[PDB]
Amino acid sequence: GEIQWMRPSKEVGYPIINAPSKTKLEPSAFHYVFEGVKEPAVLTKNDPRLKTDFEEAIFSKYVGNKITEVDEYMKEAVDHYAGQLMSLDINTEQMCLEDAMYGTDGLEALDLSTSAGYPYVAMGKKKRDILNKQTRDTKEMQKLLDTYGINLPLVTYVKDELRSKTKVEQGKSRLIEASSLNDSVAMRMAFGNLYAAFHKNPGVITGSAVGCDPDLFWSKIPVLMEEKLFAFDYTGYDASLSPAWFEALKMVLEKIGFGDRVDYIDYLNHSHHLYKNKTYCVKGGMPSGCSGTSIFNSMINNLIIRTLLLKTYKGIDLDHLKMIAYGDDVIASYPHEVDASLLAQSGKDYGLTMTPADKSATFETVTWENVTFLKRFFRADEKYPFLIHPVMPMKEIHESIRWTKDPRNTQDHVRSLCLLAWHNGEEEYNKFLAKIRSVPIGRALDLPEYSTLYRRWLDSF
RNA sequence: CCAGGUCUCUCGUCCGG
RNA sequence: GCCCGGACGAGAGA
Ligand SMILES: [Zn+2]
């Protein structure tokens, strides 16, 4: 992606939208019980912690575009992935306005608790004003579509979230692009049946994990994988996606029968944004805050990996690639070992910056022991070897527990961390509780015991 | 007094069949 | 007891 121009939106007709400047994150009752290095991200330029210019930092992600042409390997990747999706029999029809707004089998309603975006946000208009889940009233929405159309500008906000130390000093705050309610609805009418088919079929056919529940899905994954794992990280995945990758995406869409809506992807490519007193325009790339980005990113990952294997290994048989992506995250396999250092090499030629998995300094063999997906490791149950624990390391959980956005949520927050934590084993878990229970508020909390959780997990199969 | 996207999963609360 | 569903809130993950 690349910025094409900035300029006081006042000089191009667009309103000024100002985001809050204060973090909602505050130290927990557990802030000193557990160790941690993360702190709330920089939300403004006038932030003390900064050791470099903010706006330079937060926009520096738009690294340019290597390719624009879909070459022979990408094309073969497209044909192969599309053929896979074809086996699912994806309903290619538009989704009616009512289901695109209110949800259907495999697709959740629009989120009524979030912003309606432009221009409703300058009009003080809210999703709740327009939508009614009880009546599923489409009349008002239809009128707003008629009135304001689609392809509206996105509103840029900095994400209020925890960030490591260097990322706070370095101003590496992440940006949110608030999609318009009109565009979310139009995207869902166009692609809802695609979204639903993905959500209903996490696994190696979709090559997507959207819709999976790790506690159960972790047991299916090793069985789905071929003998030899491989994996790697991308640096700035979304930003490094060149136009060629979207064309390839539109090609997959045409092939599976959505050919008549591929213009939507184009719109996703040339986007206008409002940040405070300014307005910019980006050509290339796909705003994280648009409908479907999670699916599209995962689909592109599938293309990317097929492409690199074709380029790197002559005569590789894609039918024996088994991979599952969640956006840019991925666990992949092949009956014979594939070298991620060699894949990362070929990736350069497509504008992809690939590095060893899990921030390793070097590319090393990926094994069931070091492999991670969705931040969780894979560990067979001691008692029942076929049942696999998604193991999230405690470090992450300790970071989370040290902060709250509203202490009235402490119980739910800590309970939820517990459901993540216990997979580390009874000993690590019981220590977690002891530490929680080492302060009075922790002793007022109702927390599940290991054996209750373990039994619940066994029973869930 | 509010403000801050798209999704998935899960848990909790409340309410139902 | 066990299923199935809804509304709202939260957490994590991408
Ligand atoms: Zn433009």
Image (cartoon, coloured by chain):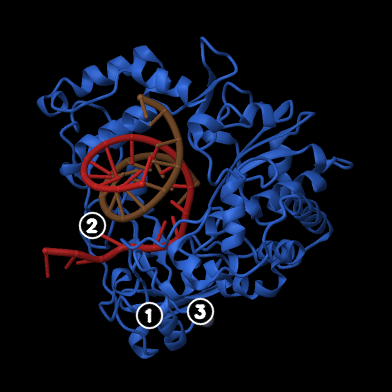
Chain colours: A blue, B red, C brown
Camera-side residue: A109 or A43?
A109
The residue indicated by pointer 2 is A47
Judging depth in this view, the residue of A200 and A419 nearest the camera is A200
Name the residue: 37% across, 13% down: A426
Callout 1, which amino acid?
Glu
Count every numbered label the image shows and give the total: 3
Which residue corresponds to mark 3? A151
| CA distance separating discs 3 and 1 | 19 Å
- Residue at point 57%, 55% (across, down): A196
- What's the residue at 56%, 53% (across, down)? A237
Residue type, numbered disc 2: Asp
Mark 2 belongs to which subunit? Answer: A
- CB-based contact (under 8 Å), mark 3 and mark 2: no
Q: Is residue C10 above or below residue A194?
A: above
Compare residues A345 and A441 and report the one nearer the observer: A441
Q: Secondary structure at mark 2?
A: loop
Give the x, y percent position of residue A126. Answer: 29, 72
Number of the front mark, 1 or 2:
1
Alpha-carbon span between mark 3 and mark 2: 34 Å
Q: Earlier in the sequence, mark 3 or mark 2?
A: 2
Identify the residue under disc 1. A140
Please state the chain letter of the residue tagged with numbered disc 3 in the rendered image: A
Label 1, secondary structure: give it: helix
Residue A202 placed where, x, y %? 60, 43
Residue A180 seen from this side: no
Q: Which circle marks residue A409 in the picture?
A: none
A270 with respect to A87 (left or right) = left
Quadrant (top left, top right, bottom left, bottom right) of the N terminus of chain A? bottom right
Q: Quadrant of residue A38?
A: top left
**Are there few (<14), some (14-19), or many (20+) residues within 10 Å of tag 1?**
few
Q: CA distance from mark 1 to mark 2?
A: 42 Å
